[PDB]
Image (tube, rainbow over all chains, first blue to last red):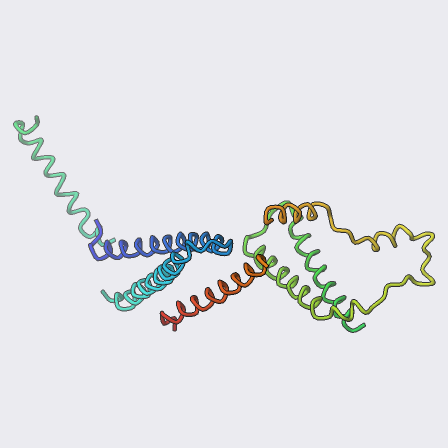
Length: 108
Length: 136
């Protein structure tokens, strides 16, 4: 499996696009609510401020976190290799098989 | 005549752009999406410029009075004259805004001022929201 650092990096990226999807959804609801606000019912007027504020705060911190990720790219620089040992490990397992062949009491 | 000349040249280039987008859509194979977007945006902004310039010079167009040429023969070209003379809209747009008005349907004036205050309030609210977070 990959080293953990890459794991939380990909988790943060996934959070980033989920936040972008949430921003698009909230844009959909604010566009929806503005229609009836133009229609002329004032009951949903208080919800408009909350929706706008949450939309803007969702737009800002997502870009901020992505900026942090791109910054991490800046200092992460400088921080078949398996083949060099690959034959060796193959060697090992083959002899292990011979051991299983060599002992008739373990072939069950 | 200067205003109508500018209208002429701009509408001619708009028609040229329409002919362009036409003969690149008429091909049996659709080009790349990006070229279509570029053509769409260019032609559509050109239509915007057409609308704005036609708006600017309404007085010159209105002042002009239409009259057929003495040399132009109407006996043989009456069909051509009637073709340009007619101005009634295409019917589908007509019932289109008829259904639109049907759906839409001192009271009207105070709703109008209520819309004014909602517009101003929303503009101020979004100005405040933009000012809340530093975007630079």
